[PDB]
Structures are given as C-alpha cells and as structure tokens.
Length: 300
Length: 237
View (cartoon, each protein chain N blue to C red):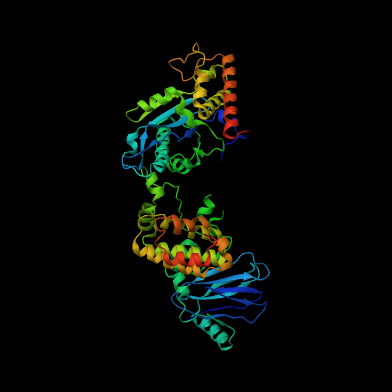
C-alpha cells in the first residue's frame, strides 16, 4: 500500500481521493493519504473552500514514482510533484505515519467500485490524452477544453480525446451514406476499434476516463466524449457480444456511482433514451437499463 | 440557418441557391388485396429542385423501379433525394454550383448534409416558410412527363416561362407560389381559372398560359379569392 504525503494544508479545501472526499481546514495538520491500493490509477482532487470555481486534480499511479502534494502560494493551488530521492521520501512518510497526520484510503474489503470504474484505464493512455511529458502524473480541471471543442484555444492545455463526429467523412464511406449514418458498425468496428484504438480495451479505457473527468471535475467536454463513445456503440447493429456485455457492466457502475443531485447536468436525455429504448442495442444493456429506470426515471 | 419572412429578399440576390422539395419522390395508391388486407402500389415520383432567381427547375423523375425490393421506403426516399441532389451538384460546373440548398422539409437536413460532406462550403438550410411545391404535380406538363417515364430521367424546365422578361424574380416567385397555393387548395377551381378563356393558350415551350400583364392581374385576383373562399370553408370563418 502506497502514500501521497502533503507538505502542508495552508488553505481550507475539500480533498478527493478517487470516490472519497475529506474537508481540511486552513492550516490543519494534514500530511496526506496512506494505504492507497496498488494496481489501479488514482485521482487526487481539490475544491478550495473560498472559491468552489475550478475543481482540479492529478491522475497518478504509485507504481510509477513517489508523488507528494505541496501548496504553491504563487499559482494558488495544491500541486503534485515527484520526489526522485527514494530514501528522503520513505523518511518523510514514516515521520507523518508515526505522528498519525495521514488519512487512510477508506477502502471497504467487499467494495469493487473503484476497480469497476477504472478496469480499462491505464496511466500511459491518460498521458496521451493529457500531454505534459515532463510529469508521470496528469493535471485535469473543470475548464480544460477537448481538441474537438477547440476545432468548433491553448493547444497545450487541451484534452486530446479521440474525435468522434457522426457527420464526418471519417464516419461515412462514399456510396454508403444512408447505411453508415443509420448503422455506425463500420465507423465503430473498422475506423475506431481496428483503426485507432487497436482494441475494445483502449476504447473502454478512454470512455471510463472521460466519465471520471466529467464526474470529478464537472468537465463538460469529457461529458460530451463519454456520451459520444456510448452512442457510437449503441447506434451500431454489429458489436461483438463481449463488448456489449462489458459495456453494460461499465455503465452500470458509472450510473451507480454518479451523485444523485448531478444527473440533471451530467446525463444527456437524448443519448440515454436513444441508447436504452430506440437503438440496435436497446435490449443488450439489462443492468444499465434497470439501474437508470430505478434511479433516474425522470430523465426517461 | 432557417429561411423565413425576415430574410425573404435573400432568395433573389446573386448567390446561386436551390430549393429542394422531396414531397413527390415516393408516391403510392393504397388499395385492398383479395384477402381484404391493405397494400400500396408505387407510382412515378419527382424531386423538385428550383433556382428561385432564374426559374430553372431540375425535375429528376423517380421511376417505380428504384423502390423494387427495398424496405422502409419513406426513409429511403429522403436518402435517394439527397443522393440525386448531390449527383446534380457534382454534375454542374463549379461556377454553377449552389452556395445554399434550402430543403422544404426538415427531415431532408441530415440526409442532404451526409451526401454533401464533399461540399463543406455549401450551406444546407431549412425554411419556416410553408411552400406549396407539393402542387408541382398539378402542372399538366410536369405530371405528364413524370407518369410517362419508363426509366430514371432528368428533365429541365423554366417554371417562370418568359415572365422574367417583364417582371423581377421576387414578383415571379410570388406569382408561382400563389398559383401553386391555389392548385394545392382547389385544383379543379384553380385549373378552371387558368383555362376559362380558350383564346389564351400555353405555348408548346411553356408551362402556363400566355397572359398579358393586365390578364395576369385578373388571374392573380381570382387565385387569391379562391384561396380565401376555401379558407372560409375548412374553418367556417
């Protein structure tokens, strides 16, 4: 089990670690988070008490280095940083642990929620969507725009999600206009899966990452990507059995985890009604349809 | 975006544009079968593609053979309309290609947009105007060429005959829409009004009678009165 120590907490902030969150008061003797499960990506995220504007955070994997948080009073945020000196790091953590100034990643043993939300999400793929090659960890926030959002303004601070556009030459083969528009199977199976993602694992990884950025940061562009990647599958008449079965499980845990009070802004009525009731796959998402109907029957 | 009453004059400016109407593409007669079920028999159709400035009408006849062994024909009809409009634009020289295509029904937007991906600089627009282009098949010579077709065929007309020699395209368009609105409301009455005086004829190379300026004013008045009469019937007002 791994640790993200904090230098200090000089400003009152709500700290997220994955699906958990703790309020820390201005100058509270908080020195970090211990017992973080090895084997998954994690996100550590922040909402300042005095300006709830810009939720922001860091995607990281503790197998890839020793990471700590330090408040920068110039840029006014909690920053992730890598400690290259292994012995210094182990010694900082040991001191804070012995003084019990660290909160415990509060994982329930039966609870597979985080695994289920990050099953296909890999740090290497995150670092290609969020480009900042000098760091092993990835910054995301509320206001960052997607490559696609910018096409329709600072390129280095963009989310480089795969562009999906149902009315693009990429989506539509010459002479198969009606076929490809009403049945997106060629765009999903040849262009996206075989062409760009290489396999359904990379496709689900991006879909899951897009959801988590939508949920944790209210990132609007990430919400658009998650819906697009769902709609591309649901709008395809030909999808491998294993992908449909996996998709039902993925969306199930996403809907289960979503804050109940956020379904108004995070869920797109048109996409969900279309995916569950009208599409080719309207009968292939049993688990997802049962939770959506019991938890968000207003949306439908 | 959407074409309406406010931006009406734009139809007659010097930017090439076409109206597309798909209402006569897929046409059927509904009938009873021997077992007492209902069946449709398709008849020849047409795409109505009109330059409102010049009067140039590209009448693409849709032969019943294009439906043979196809399913969901009302859906296919929108895609076949978009395919044919796309083929017409590609067949025109660059300086003849439209800068805008206005569809008279919103269900045409996606099919036309997906067929015109190759022309990202051609704007595909809906309209809020209720245009009477459905009534094109009430023009005897257009109806005749559609029904006699034995294969797919493009026929070129000028729907304004020689009117632009004497009037503007604004006035020519207003005359055309009033004639078509009348034909659509009361075909029998409208056609009676247009042939009432047997001395006025339709030239072999024309669609409408050869009315003098004064006879057009009379005809236009009769068409307006026909439209109010019919209106004070549908609604009893």
